[PDB]
Image: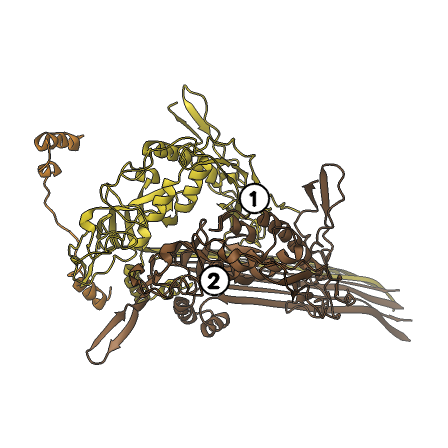
Chain colours: A yellow, B orange, C brown
Amino acid sequence: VTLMPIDCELSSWSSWTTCDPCQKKRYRYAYLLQPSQFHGEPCNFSDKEVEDCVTNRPCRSQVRCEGFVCAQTGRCVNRRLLCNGDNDCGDQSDEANCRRIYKKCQHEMDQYWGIGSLASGINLFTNSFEGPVLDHRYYAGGCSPHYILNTRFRKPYNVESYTPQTQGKYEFILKEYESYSDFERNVTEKMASKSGFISSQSDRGKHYIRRTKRFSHTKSVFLHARSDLEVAHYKLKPRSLMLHYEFLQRVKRLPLEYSYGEYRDLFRDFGTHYITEAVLGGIYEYTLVMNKEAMERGDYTLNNVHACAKNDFGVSVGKCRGILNEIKDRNKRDTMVEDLVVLVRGGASEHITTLAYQELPTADLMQEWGDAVQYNPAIIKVKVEPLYELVTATDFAYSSTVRQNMKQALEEFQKEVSSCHCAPCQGNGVPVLKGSRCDCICPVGSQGLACEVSYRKNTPIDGKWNCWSNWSSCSGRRKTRQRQCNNPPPQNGGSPCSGPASETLDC
Amino acid sequence: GNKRRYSAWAESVTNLPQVIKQKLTPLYELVKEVPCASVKKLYLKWALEE
Amino acid sequence: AATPAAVTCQLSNWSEWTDCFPCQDKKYRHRSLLQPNKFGGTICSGDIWDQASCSSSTTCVRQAQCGQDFQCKETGRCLKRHLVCNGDQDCLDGSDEDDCEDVRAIDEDCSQYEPIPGSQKAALGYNILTQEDAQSVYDASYYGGQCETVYNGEWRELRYDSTCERLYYGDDEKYFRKPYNFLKYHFEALADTGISSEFYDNANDLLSKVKKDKSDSFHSQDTSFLNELNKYNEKKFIFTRIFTKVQTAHFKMRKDDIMLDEGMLQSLMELPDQYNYGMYAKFINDYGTHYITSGSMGGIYEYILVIDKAKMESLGITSRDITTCFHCKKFGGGKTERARKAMAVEDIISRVRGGSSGWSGGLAQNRSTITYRSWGRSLKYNPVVIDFEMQPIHEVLRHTSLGPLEAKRQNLRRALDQYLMEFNACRCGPCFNNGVPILEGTSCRCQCRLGSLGAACEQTQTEGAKADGSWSCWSSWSVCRAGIQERRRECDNPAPQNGGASCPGRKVQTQAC
């Protein structure tokens, strides 16, 4: 068989770290050396392991809150947010026991549409939204008037702007090519000869015919359409951000000692990055490629030959001979190949699907899609900062150490989550590291667990990088890459991989 | 484009207009109301050229 | 092949009754499934687990055990005490919320938001052996006193008010409450479609002929010979394959402090610390081999069409005609042969996973913008899980609020490895013609695709088709004496047939002794 399932391999455990003087725990972990693929056996999920300890030493985690402490959550909130009329705590502990409530916003307020999604951190490497990292329901008072159309919105405290900067860009390109070639040839020869004169008669005849018909037809269509729609601009404040309870707790529990597996679990739960600016929008993309070819072939040959004699004196003698020979060879070949890809982001399932249909939309459903995108937009452009920039002394003790731990772990994570580790798919399939195992995402018209099935006899193989080599020594710290993981040339190879085929840096 | 499509757009831009013409003032002119405001203003002038 | 013979279902004797569990007053025992009725066959009358009443002759205290935290009477659910009188019953007895005349303990007015519709399926356990949902593993409704909410991006529903003249959108659906067990629930509209379509056709055609005539006179003779052939071939092949994948939300289950379902909680409290395969196999049967910790909610449409046709024809002739005169005489003699054959197969599969019976059927019938749009609308009200990551059920125990369960977890691992051996569809016989073997309860079936029929799908209606093989399962573990234990398996159930592919898995599997 061509395929063999590769089972998941994870490392021998780390050394234990030292026991956390407060968290009273020590940690061990393994790296994933090789993901499972092609239904290879998955690893044990326990690439993390934990042991309890005695409290060998105190730790100064008891970060002083001058504000009110939200009794159940431990969120520190300013006393001006007591009796605010708003759950600025998690648990209304700010609003209990209040003699009088000073409702600041009498008005009806909506939240910004999709604003909660932007509060959740992204795995940048996978572009995947993860757990919540920022609390976009904290308002710290607020109650400034913000409007979009006739609706009024309560801006979260964390948000500097969410503003309906509205724009749309459309692109249509269509390239139709036809060529056809036709070649008919005919050749005909005839000969006759006679003699006649006791009597004698002689005759010779010959006929030859050759005929050739060759025809080829080639047709090509490329159509691409793209719509980029933009419906708001979002910016997060640069300073004094209010973290989500779950993220807050999960950061608190981070061991002061560097133990990669816990920071990896942090990234797996919440990602590596958070969004500081984004453009909210919708995307529609349509790409149709068609090639049609015909060939017709015909060769025809005919021969006749005659030789015929009579001799007379009555009495007569004679010989006469005739041949006919005929050949026809004919072939037809006809092929069509068609690919369509349609991509849609933002909008509503009805308009999403009716745009996903294989035909170009009516401008009504484009209008309906763009209207729906306002209320359920996607993120078109993002600008992000790494999640460690949230670990701040106003929230966490030892914050510089936790931050530096994250800084290292983020490098180790970027290395470990890289899909370079997977074996290449066949059929130009893209291996995606998806947990501890790797799934070949196959272009349609290629199929199976490795994209091993296709009915197309040839398909360009695009280049794939191998994993970059380890850091070279100082005097020009360096890494290298080889385009080895899928060498492009096969099957009328596609483009080579991008550079940098080697990369070099300060020590 | 359809006359109705364009007219509906041109009406809707009444409620969601973008900025389409501007006259600009350097950002350093806004450095204000802060400690050392006058010094920071100069340094931000020098920053913008850089 | 003709059908295999039937086999009767067979079970072992009852194992010895488990000693009466004090809190249950129940005795348990199990059998082993020695054989499912692979084909035809008498089904076993009896279940492979049995329980009976008892008396323990000893009390148990466990109702008191947790009582530092608020422990309900009905259930083992033990709650952080701020959940008492919180305003939301957190265990099914409501004992946390009865007599709460100190109503000041309420946490928040959140009941204005319903739970996420269709969140309950993510709470269910999963049986890899059958791809069926089990009982609930996660609590689908426990909130832990949080009012954490998810924005429903599709909340816009038209309304009309004849008392005015306004067409406007209603807002009831605008937010859902997120159950505690979801770390993430994330509405997001994506679609992708891919279509591939291909045609190849060839027609190849040759004719060839000779006529040879010879005549002589001395009396006279004339002769003519002919040889001729026609040989025509045609191949037609069409393939098209459509995939459409709408995503409407993603979810992720919490990896920590998982609050197990009341039923799973009680059943896990009932299992012994001592290994007892009957008990743990019953647990795996009820709650499934696996539980889910990732999500996409959506709809999928898939369409495939293949057509293959061929025609072959040939004709041949050879002849002689003669005449002579000395009285004049005429003869002829020869042979001609002719053949024709024609073949067509057309196979289409369309399937919709999604949001209404009506338009799932309509889109399964007639792919069109009308059915695409109306099914997409139906996906608003009833999305279906389109992708999910899962892990073995025992990995849930590591993460529960119950703390450590090392011994029970190792027992459940061992039991799962046996359960995944004993109930594997390997024990359903050879499903021929690419039929799918299924094992359910103590019985077997083949699901036979339309080109196939009979108790093993053994009689394809055509003369035959290329059918790939499938493995029998792995044999027993070796009685290892070296440090290594070994298991063997072969691609013979059925073997690759009519040129079909080998099954692709491993022949040899190895374990530490």
Crowding near pointer 1: few (<14 within 10 Å), some, many (20+)? some
Dot 1 corresponds to which residue?
Answer: A43
x 20%, y 77%: residue: C165
For the residues beneath circles 2 and 1, the answer to whether they share a chain is no
**Residue A255 is at least partly visible in this image:** yes
Q: CA distance from mark 2 to mark 1?
A: 40 Å
The image shows residue A498, relative to residue C254, as above or below, that is above
Looking at the image, is mark 2 or mark 1 nearer the viewer?
Answer: 2
From this viewpoint, is residue A174 visible? no
The local secondary structure at tag 1 comes to: loop
Which residue corresponds to mark 2? C73
Secondary-structure class at tag 2: loop
Under mark 2, the amino acid is Lys
Give the residue at x 21% y 68%. B4
The crowding category of the residue bearing disc 2, from other C-alpha atoms within 10 Å (few below 14, some 14 to 19, many at least 20), is: some
Marked residue chain, label 2 = C
Query: Which residue is pictured at 8% across the width and 31% down the height?
Result: B38
Whether pointer 2 and pointer 1 mark residues with C-beta atoms closer than 8 Å, the reply is no
Q: Nearer the viewer, residue C63 or C175?
A: C63
Farthest residue to the right: give it.
Answer: C326
Q: Is residue C470 left or right of residue A141?
A: right
Q: Label 1 sits on what residue type?
A: Cys
A394 or C214, nearer to the observer: A394
> Is residue C134 left or right of B44 when viewed as pictured?
right
